[PDB]
Image: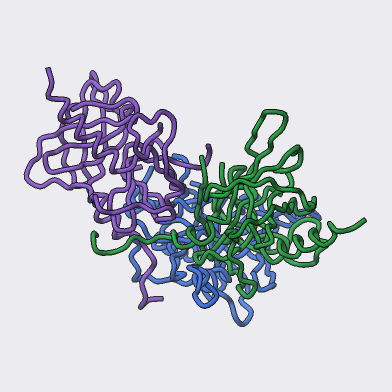
Chain colours: A blue, B purple, C green
Amino acid sequence: STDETPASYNLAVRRAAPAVVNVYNRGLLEIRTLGSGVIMDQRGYIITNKHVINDADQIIVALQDGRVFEALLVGSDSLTDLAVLKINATGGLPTIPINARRVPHIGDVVLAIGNPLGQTITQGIISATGRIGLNPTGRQNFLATDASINHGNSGGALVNSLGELMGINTLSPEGIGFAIPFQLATKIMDKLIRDGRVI
Amino acid sequence: STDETPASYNLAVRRAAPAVVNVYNRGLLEIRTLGSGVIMDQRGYIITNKHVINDADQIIVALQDGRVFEALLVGSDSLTDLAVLKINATGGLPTIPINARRVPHIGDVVLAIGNPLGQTITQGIISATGRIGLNPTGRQNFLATDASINHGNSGGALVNSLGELMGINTLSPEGIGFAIPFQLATKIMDKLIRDGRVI
Amino acid sequence: STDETPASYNLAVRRAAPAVVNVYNRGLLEIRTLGSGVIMDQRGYIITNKHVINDADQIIVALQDGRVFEALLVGSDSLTDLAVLKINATGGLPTIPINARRVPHIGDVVLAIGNPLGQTITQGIISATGRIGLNPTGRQNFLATDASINHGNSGGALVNSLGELMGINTLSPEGIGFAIPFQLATKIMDKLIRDGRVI
């Protein structure tokens, strides 16, 4: 036992966990814990759930390395219950690994990450994929997983054994949790970033 | 990340999932979703739970490849809450992989498969094995697992990382799901097939 | 399929499971099932939860190999809800593998073991680690995991793929179970053993 190594997905945790952050409100002083989020790129854009930031007077984001920024709401999307925040990027931002070439397969191992107790991670697999409810996008709508999904990780990341982003944990039929495919999450972010610059 | 491969049990899914089917009723027109089932052999025999087909006027079975047959009830077994259906086998039927030589061990990884949301798969391990309640068979009665078992997969298959059949998800003490060992399920099917041909 | 081998953690089960035992009370005759415990060393010391043995007139311990001893309460610790029992060690006692050099990492695979249905094992990962509530020890207080933790395994062991002891399942915020790090459990046991010899 002493010589060998335990089976673990701590690799994926090292790679993707730094990029997952907390999201707070700071009304007035009251500092509430809203939920989780995911740093997407060096520009300082972050994805989170719309419900998390719905009634937010002041939004604050806290990284696992100790840094704390104030974020501004770039824009949200009710249908997918997503929202994009923006923060000033001091030199060095941890970003969520993304592989646009990777094709998620049913059965894949996935870790769910978010802060309820500090950062927390649960393990499951991709239970199913397809489209659900109103699907204006025309593209695959949901991603199901038996990894525990709750408020504590709602808005957080869902990643494979490699650490690559598979989806965004969301709340929008028991024992199963849902995430928004990273391909759809990417597209929605871009359209929210671009259409945020509009009269 | 781009080069390597994610840890996954999609192999087992490819092999065993095609064989797991939906089971409906078609009263009158009302088409209800009853539960799941498992194609066992080329002859077109299918195992499912007795509760699934208890009050069924007309039974219908739908494969993942798009085909839809009408099934007839070969016979059921109250003690194990199993039931065997029969369908006309057009050329080419997907059947559930079975290894009569394989000995299930506690700790083994297992996937639970069934259609609640479309086909769905959850992951767990064999938590325990033994005999429970009235045991006329004299042989091992149950197989416990922490893979989520629910109505949506009740009657579906339980398989290992290889795809080999370990048991039949059933409903007949919290956080744990149950399946009927494939060795017992086989024997019960045969006796229901044979004793179905009786005056 | 026939040639290959299923993915399994039965190795860890073989190594650590024999050491996990049942704990009963024997009032008067009534024999109640209290919970689970863990043989720690050849001297015959066993760890269990304090709630398990709180109102115990006579304590009995049953191994998976068939042997049955009477245990005496060495002492307990309210803060960590632990308790140490002592039994006469006939030649040959199964003890829980321990690696004082092993550093638990988040994401590690872990099996939870205890007797509710006979011995049962569930699989999860180390979700988180840190310190919680009143922390007089100054050292890391808790270990979180998404392996199912319940009364049936409360007091039982939590081990990695190797079988090495990671913690003691305990009851002292949903979907997540807790265990006491084995490094803290060791220290508490020793202090209870030593300070048990006191006027």
Task: Give the answer, above or below, for where C51 lies relative to C38.
Answer: above
The quadrant in which residue B90 appears is top left
Give the residue at x 18% y 44%.
B66
Give the residue at x 53% y 55%.
C17
Depth check: give the residue in front, A29 or C87.
C87
The reply to whether residue A199 is visible in this rendering is no
Depth check: give the residue in front, A116 or C115.
C115
Task: Give the answer, above or below, for where B189 lies relative to C103.
Answer: above
Depth check: give the residue in front, B121 or B191.
B191
Give the residue at x 48% y 42%.
B176
Q: Position of residue C155 (x, y in %)?
A: 65, 50
The quadrant in which residue A27 appears is bottom right
Q: Position of residue C118 (x, y in %)?
A: 52, 43
As drawn, the residue found furthest toward the front would be C91
Q: Position of residue C138 (x, y in %)?
A: 80, 67
Give the residue at x 73% y 54%.
C84
Depth check: give the residue in front, B165 or C21.
C21
Q: Position of residue C142 (x, y in %)?
A: 69, 59
